[PDB]
Amino acid sequence: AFLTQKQKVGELKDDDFEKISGVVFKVSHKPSGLVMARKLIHLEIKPAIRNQIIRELQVLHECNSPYIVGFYGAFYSDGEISICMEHMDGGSLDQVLKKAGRIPEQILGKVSIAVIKGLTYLREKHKIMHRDVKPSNILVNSRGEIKLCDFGVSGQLIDAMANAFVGTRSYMSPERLQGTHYSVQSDIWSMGLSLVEMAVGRYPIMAIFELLDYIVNEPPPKLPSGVFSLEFQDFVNKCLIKNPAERADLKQLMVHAFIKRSDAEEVDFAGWLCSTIG
Amino acid sequence: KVGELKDDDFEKISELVVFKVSHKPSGLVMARKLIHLEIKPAIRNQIIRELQVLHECNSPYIVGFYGAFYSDGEISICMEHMDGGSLDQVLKKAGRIPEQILGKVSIAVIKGLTYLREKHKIMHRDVKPSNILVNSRGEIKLCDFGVSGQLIDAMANAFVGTRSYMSPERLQGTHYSVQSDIWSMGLSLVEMAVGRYPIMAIFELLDYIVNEPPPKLPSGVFSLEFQDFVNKCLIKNPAERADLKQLMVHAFIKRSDAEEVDFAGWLCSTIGLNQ
Amino acid sequence: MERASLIQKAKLAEQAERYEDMAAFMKGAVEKGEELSCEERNLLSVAYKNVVGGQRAAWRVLSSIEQKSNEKGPEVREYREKVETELQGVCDTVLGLLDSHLIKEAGDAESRVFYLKMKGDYYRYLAEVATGDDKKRIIDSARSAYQEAMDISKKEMPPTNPIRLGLALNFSVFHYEIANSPEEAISLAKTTFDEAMADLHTLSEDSYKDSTLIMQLLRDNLTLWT
Amino acid sequence: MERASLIQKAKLAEQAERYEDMAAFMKGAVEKGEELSCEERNLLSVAYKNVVGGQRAAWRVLSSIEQKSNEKGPEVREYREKVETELQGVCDTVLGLLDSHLIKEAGDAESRVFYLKMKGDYYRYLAEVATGDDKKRIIDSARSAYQEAMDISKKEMPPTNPIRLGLALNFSVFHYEIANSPEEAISLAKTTFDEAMADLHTLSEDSYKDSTLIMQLLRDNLTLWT
Amino acid sequence: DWEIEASEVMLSTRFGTVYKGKWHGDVAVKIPTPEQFQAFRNEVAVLRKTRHVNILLFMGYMTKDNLAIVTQWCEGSSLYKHLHVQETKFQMFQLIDIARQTAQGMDYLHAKNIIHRDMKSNNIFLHEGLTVKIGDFGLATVKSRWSGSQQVEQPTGSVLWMAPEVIRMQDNNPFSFQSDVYSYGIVLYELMTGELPYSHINNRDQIIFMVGRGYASPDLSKLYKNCPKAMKRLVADCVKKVKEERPLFPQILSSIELLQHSLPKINRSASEPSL
Amino acid sequence: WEIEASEVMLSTRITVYKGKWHGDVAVKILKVVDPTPEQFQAFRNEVAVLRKTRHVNILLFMGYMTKDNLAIVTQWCEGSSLYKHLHVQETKFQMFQLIDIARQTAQGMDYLHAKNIIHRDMKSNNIFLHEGLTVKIGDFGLATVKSQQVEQPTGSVLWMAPEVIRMQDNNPFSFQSDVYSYGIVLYELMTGELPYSHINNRDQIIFMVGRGYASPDLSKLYKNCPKAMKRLVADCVKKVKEERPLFPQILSSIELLQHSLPKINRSASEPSL
Ligand SMILES: CNS(=O)(=O)Nc1nccc(Cc2c(C)c3ccc(Oc4ncccc4F)cc3oc2=O)c1F
Ligand SMILES: CNS(=O)(=O)Nc1nccc(Cc2c(C)c3ccc(Oc4ncccc4F)cc3oc2=O)c1F
């Protein structure tokens, strides 16, 4: 039903959207009565490089999945690129974390299944990696769907945006931080830190450079054994192997008993979110 | 005997802006008058060309001319050294002046002015108390007269000049002649005769000159011939003002000519020097 | 055509930038046969300088193109040889006028040095476009021209005059470009600069400025070679 | 000599500013009898406009000298008609090439627009020096040729075509200088500018830049005469 | 800004010729009785409150040994030097741009309550050939409620450029906005014509009396016909003998920017560019 | 320096407003609906330091805005910043222009350090080429006067010191941090590309410069101008604080290399008039 509403929405320019609410805001198309969003990223780059960027990001139309957010389009206006974006009513999971404080374990299993499915879809169709898996890139709706967003579809856009935001929290893999080979194991690592960070609410151990030093030269933190199930700790420690050679890949994460148990569970995420809102 | 003049030949000795220098190819003392001026180089070349005419003026009662040049962005005119100095410091160190010396300098100014008129047809236009020069030899000579019209056009902008001695018929753009110069001569004579202006801003001064009659000296301090002399020299209208032929036959000027005064002795006693 | 009329036509042309026209005009005026004045000499020098400098710039561009093509058609070589024959013809014409009557009627040593400078410079340009034993005979002639001019100038004439200063500068230029004599060129340039700086204190302001306009160039090419 | 070889020689002498030589080479190349491409037409137009502009500046200088002298010798005026005969001959050969093969072989409507624009321009440069009945016949011919030029340009070009804008400004200058119709020149220029501002959105960025380099001159000219 | 510098600057020789220094780059320097101290204090105070591009930048004052000021070394020459010494041909847009810049700078000065009193073509420095500079605030003042209590002093400059009420001294303080308005208008005159006013007079106190009574105005017939009529009537009504008729600077700038928007351009008719 | 709001009006937007006040100006305006006191503190430090700045090579300042939205009014530079020319416009500067730009910004920073002020965030976005000939230094929002815990840096990590990357000292800002940022700038304009363009990870750069592995490569600098620039840019980018030289020395080296540099490619002779 997402594609058939796209067919009713044709060419999209700057004037016909109105401001409602890098920076993220919200639009709505007045005739169609649909609520969208847009992503505004400011660069200072050559126009030929800008055309390369727009031709590289036109590929996102083919990215269609129940675990990947929808793509509308993008255009260059007012000295900036505006990426037309489908609106997500529930918002990102950091706002949900600030609203609630802690997340139930079944919800953790469901979102782990969703992100695993999204990573497998991206590797089986576009064979690329997300490179920025984080709770701000996890989006949920009142319909109960969990999809990924904000991945490196354009390497030239990665080179462009790499000179921008500082970074207070870091979800970086040590192997590419050192400068070695990187694969999906880096994304599994960053998924591990993101999941444990939004499960306990904070980082259990300050300036960014010493955090980088701690990621390089210290073992990663572990959960206490007496709180949750031992299979959960085994699962996250399988996610949290420092050397990517023994770190489990997508198929071992998929065949893990925790994933199978969570998929066997029936959870009403939409009802719980509606209870959270009211 | 003095050839072409260059700045390296001149060494500063003292200041009279006028300096005192010497010319080392000749060894004689030299008067160094410098004036600042800004115009195109062709114009000052023309000025140099028309002040080459200064070579032919030769009289006992005009300061001799030796040469000129342009150097360091500054136009340089050279002057014969004049040891007794101008009358301004003379009246500063003497206060007042005898009438006999006034008759002698009247003789000097009329003889020099008639020489200039009959030999070059050029008036002075700046007969000032400062422009009248005396020496230990008793020669009273003129200087700084209006020879190069482009040079008057050059410096006409600035003169500092808080006090002026310029004639009323020259104010309204009317015809100007030697009557202006002899009128200013009368002003200079009465000024050092009393030693002051016996009557403050420049515009009020020229307003008093244009709209009010000139003052009259008291009778009890000067002779009647002197009073009639200055009254004929201070006639406001130039037509009624007596010209040179009347002032060469006046009773006062004949009495001054008949007088024999040791003016050189008086000036060397005033300056206090042993030659 | 009348001589002063041709001079006025040349003035009209130099304010109308018709360089081949002024060149033909004073070619007629110099085939009249009378001795010329300093301003006419300056006008002819700058005008044939403009002409042969234009052909020299064209030849340098064509030499660069040909040397890049000689790492596929002889058109580049043909055009280079065509403009080379043009430059040889105009230089031979100027030299022919010179050795016809100018160097013989040059009575005063100023115009003597001036004409020696001219015919040596056109020897220099002919040697720039020449190559071979012809080139070495031409630079021998250019040598004899330059040393005769500087001998006359040094014997009878103070250093700070611009014709002597330009003659020494062109001397060093010819050494560095054609004879490959950088030490000799630098030595003559610095010696002439020192002599001019010593002798400039006896000159007027405009003459001093006219000298320093090319003392700037002398200091610059000494800086370039060092 | 080969057509493409003349083309590359013309490009070479364009890079070497030898405009009369490269004009002669494309004169031969167009005398070969084949139709011209866009860049060849650009080279022809640039070469002949530069040649006519150079002799036009010379003619303007000579005309100014003559008119200040007509407030002494006929040298100034006779040199003026000498340069005028040079310009008349050059424009006559160019127009002869045009009416000999170009305007009849311009099968493309774009080439027909280009050729009519240039040929009206060359009539305008002839009218710049004409005096008598030559003036009225030449201005009538330019009037006609320009009129069908704008007719075909309006019927088959986009409004923001740079050549269309250029012929518009040449026609406005035509009315101001020689046709003496300032209100019609101003009206044509303002209508063309405003309708170009209506149609500016239909171009790419480089075509819009080429249009900016024409609308800036159009605005400058309108502020100049209004 | 404030503070005392030290011996880091360079000294050349112990109105001269050169005073250029060297301190954090090239600079410009000017030059024991209290009358120098007062004017030095006033000029330091007025340059403390100068922050604009059209005015020379002040950064330091030094007091020990000789009394001096330091400002940046401008590149170029004065407008007097460009107009009466070099006679460089300036195109119309350059001239009106110079006028706009000077008017804007003096408008800023009067808006921030500064009265310069002595603006001159010798004082307007054209830096680099594009941007004009305003300086020499040695006699500039700040008006106030008690400024009319003190009696203003003599200018002792060039007589061509003060208002008739200034040279008439009919009141305590003739200096106001309108005196600088009249000075800027005669600056516009010499900028347009290219020569100093009253060229047909070679005498100074002639000019003093002759415009002191309002008997003459600068000739507007010498203005060129290609000049726009708006700035012609601006020059006409800004040199009025009546103080009230002279307009203030904001509408002068408004008229000048309207003329800028309605300017023509460079000569010839612009054919097809060789694209 | 108090200014009323009505006489200054906004015309166009560039944050930055192209305003008019006795001519065109540049208005840096802070749009904060609920102003908090440390913003007032930083505003006061900006005003206090900008009042003390009087030089030709700096961006000149006139006055401040207090009522309604907070703003800073400075002069309007003609042209654009060096970043646009070097990385967006790609204008082919010649080498004497580069030397003159380096000398001018060296003079400006030398005076600015003679006032004992640390600019702390200078980069190519804060250097304005006025009329394409003169440089101007602006954006003093993070500057301070030497006389507590330092606030965390926020600008791009390329120009800031390896020591402030290492955040080990309480207040790591000093002269030599400015020297090293200046060295990055001289690395920037003389080759025309940003350092570490082959790496597109921000924290990888942060860690590699923190540990000391990172070093700007002088290989991509041209060899046409002599080796004086080579030893200069090598010396001014050195990691240790004490071996980075002071600005009178770098000035002296600049004019010493300028005294022996020719602008002619051939042999010129008699100039035809
Ligand atoms: C520590 N980070 S890093 O150093 O590894 N650098 C980088 N990593 C990863 C990515 C990038 C850049 C990136 C960004 C910023 C981006 C954002 C939005 C976007 O829209 C949509 N997104 C998903 C679905 C549908 C969409 F419409 C596409 C984007 O595409 C991009 O390429 C990086 F710079
Ligand atoms: C209210 N009067 S005014 O406004 O007309 N001003 C003027 N009037 C008249 C004249 C002038 C200028 C003047 C000056 C000052 C001058 C100075 C020296 C000079 O050399 C010698 N002189 C005499 C003897 C020997 C010499 F070597 C010639 C000069 O020639 C001059 O003309 C004025 F400025």
Image (cartoon, coloured by chain):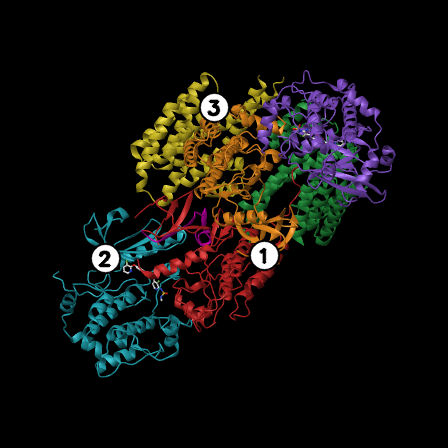
Chain colours: A purple, B cyan, C yellow, D green, E red, F orange
Q: Is residue E68 magenta?
A: yes
Write down the chain letter for disc 2: B
Label 3 within 8 A of ligand 2 by Cβ: no
Residue nearer the viewer, D102 or D158: D158
Q: Are marks 3 and 1 on the same chain?
A: no
Q: Is residue F106 magenta?
A: no
Which element type, helix, strand or loop, lies under badge 1? loop
Relative to B25, is A182 above or below?
A: above
Relative to residue E242, is residue A196 drawn left or right? right
Foreground: disc 3 or disc 1: 1
Report if residue C37 is visible in the image: no
Which element type, helix, strand or loop, lies under badge 2? strand
Q: Position of residue C187 (x, y in %)?
A: 35, 26
Q: Which residue is mark 2?
A: B80
Please name the amino acid that badge 3 sits on. Glu
- What quarter of the picture does the C terminus of chain B occupy? bottom left
Write down the chain letter for disc 1: E
Q: Residue at x 67, y 54 (%)?
A: D226
Q: Which residue is mark 3?
A: C128
Which region shows up in magenta?
Answer: E65-86
